[PDB]
């Protein structure tokens, strides 16, 4: 990984030691980036809802993951499931159960630093996995991106600044999350997010993530070319708010 500090250094050491999941996949790969493009063609707002318990950017929320996921199946373009253990109180078992209960695309949100975590994502039923430029070298990114593609997944490349966007372009990312939240400091900068969005070619599927809370900001971002919108805490507090974000 990269040289890191603070909680990101801790979570990378944890991920390096995380045991593998050793069962077989029991569902097809359902492409999230293609379903986003289909929603775009249907002029349906494409919302990626997240399930987590703890978060460095929120108070804990304890709710039933299956009631939540089955509700979101009716409205969301896909579901992100936070599986990191210490800072998100996530679990592979939770991802496994959600993936078995719904038929929309599932993104595994974790801090992927070794190929076995991609094996894990595949075997658990996730359709794609996040790769975070801030924690990986260019060599590691390209290797993990190629490894995920060899399973038929199109990884979800997470960027937060200009250096990250440069690396995402270098490595041939086709599916990019422009995250407004710096993971080291937890600060949000939407001006920087919009600058990055303006520098991404049209053929890349773009997801805006980070402090999205209002229908009007979705519409503004869609006008700038963003294809889909990620929303965590707001929907974890009140799932039914997604109906307003779409309608
Ligand atoms: O909790 N999440 O599933 C989740 C998904 C994507 C994100 N991007 N930035 N933070 C994120 C959190």
Image (cartoon, rainbow, N blue to C red):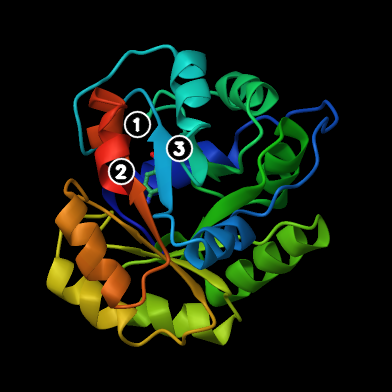
Q: Residue at x 39, y 55 (%)?
A: 45
Label 3 to label 2: alpha-carbon separation: 34 Å
Rendering coords of residue 7 (x, y %): 30, 43
The answer to whether marks 3 and 2 mark residues whose Cβ atoms lie closer than 8 Å is: no
Mark 3 packing: few (<14 Cα in 10 Å), some, or many (20+)? some
Question: Which badge, 2 or 1, comes first in the chain's sequence?
Answer: 2
Q: How many marks?
A: 3
State how far apart marks 2 and 1 are (Cα).
Answer: 9 Å
Under tag 3, what secondary structure? loop
Crowd around label 2: few <14 · some 14–19 · many ≥20 (10 Å): some
Question: Residue under circle 3?
Answer: 75
Residue designated by label 2: 7
Can you tell me which quadrant of the image ligand 1 is in?
A: top left
Q: Which is more toward the observer, 196 or 187? A: 196
Left or right relative to 190: residue 179: right
Q: Residue at label 1? A: 87
Single out the mark in the foreground, 2 or 1.
Answer: 1
């Amino acid at each position: 990984p990269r040289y890191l500090k603070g909680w990101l250094k801790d979570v990378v050491q944890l991920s390096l030691r995380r045991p593998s999941f050793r069962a077989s996949r029991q569902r097809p790969i359902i492409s999230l980036n293609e379903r986003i493009l289909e929603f775009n063609k249907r002029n349906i707002t494409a919302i990626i809802a997240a399930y987590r318990r703890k978060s460095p950017s929120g108070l804990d929320v304890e709710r039933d993951p299956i009631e939540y996921s089955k509700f979101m199946e009716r409205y969301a373009v896909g579901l992100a499931v936070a599986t990191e253990e210490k800072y998100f109180n996530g679990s592979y078992e939770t991802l496994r159960k959600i993936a078995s209960s719904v038929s929309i695309p599932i993104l595994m949100w974790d801090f992927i630093v070794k190929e076995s975590q991609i094996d894990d994502a595949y075997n658990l039923g996730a359709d794609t996995v996040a790769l975070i430029v801030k924690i990986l070298t260019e060599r590691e990114l390209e290797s993990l991106l190629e490894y995920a593609r060899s399973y038929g997944m199109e990884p979800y490349i997470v960027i937060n600044d200009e250096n990250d966007l440069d690396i995402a372009l270098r490595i041939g990312a086709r599916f990019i999350e422009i995250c407004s939240r710096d993971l080291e400091t937890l600060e949000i900068n939407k001006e920087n997010q919009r600058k990055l969005i303006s520098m991404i070619p049209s053929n890349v599927v773009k997801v805006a993530w980070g402090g999205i809370s209002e229908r009007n900001e979705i519409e503004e971002l869609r006008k700038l070319g963003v294809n889909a919108f990620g929303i965590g805490s707001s929907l974890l507090r009140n799932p039914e708010k997604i109906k307003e974000f779409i309608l």
